[PDB]
Amino acid sequence: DPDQLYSTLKSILQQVKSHQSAWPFMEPVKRTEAPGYYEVIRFPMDLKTMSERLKNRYYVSKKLFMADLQRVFTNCKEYNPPESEYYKCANILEKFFFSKIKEAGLID
Image 1 (cartoon, rainbow, N blue to C red):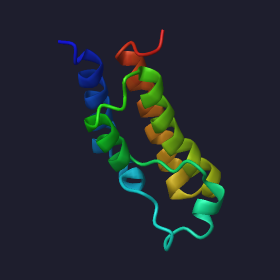
Image 2 (image 1 turned 90 degrees about the vertical axis):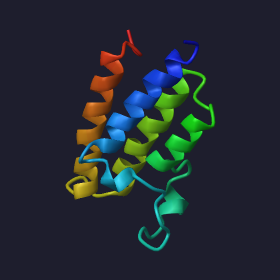
Image 3 (image 1 turned 180 degrees about the horizontal axis):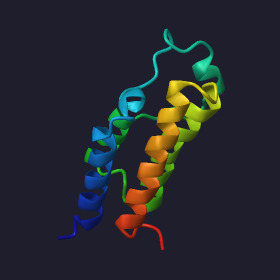
């Protein structure tokens, strides 16, 4: 259908959300749990917000989707110590993300 981009992105986002390393990214970061977070991280992003954006038909291009999801990882890696469990999850899930976007032919 015309929903080919939407269907592809929904599949990708769902697979990312089901991944066992996705648990840290599943909802917005809480100020209580992250001192200084919103002072350092200017464009917060999480997989719940991404799901809404997707449902709200925001992702009219592959580039808008890839930017949000990449941001989930890079925010985490800037904020957290390099050997933290969060930083480890980011890179695992990031590897999985780049493999899925390649599988789908979203990058050439």
